[PDB]
Amino acid sequence: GKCLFSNPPICFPN
Image 1 (cartoon, rainbow, N blue to C red):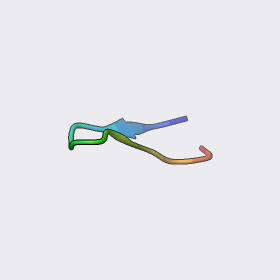
Image 2: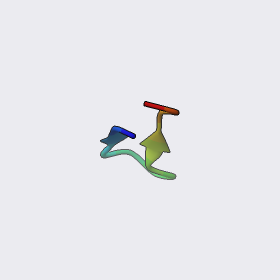
Image 3: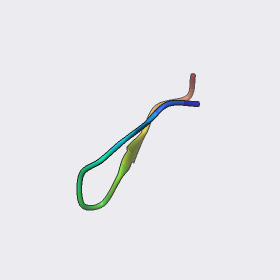
Image 4: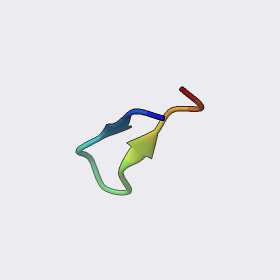
């Protein structure tokens, strides 16, 4: 569920 600010934003399955 955690999205990391990146492009494209890396949203982890958590």
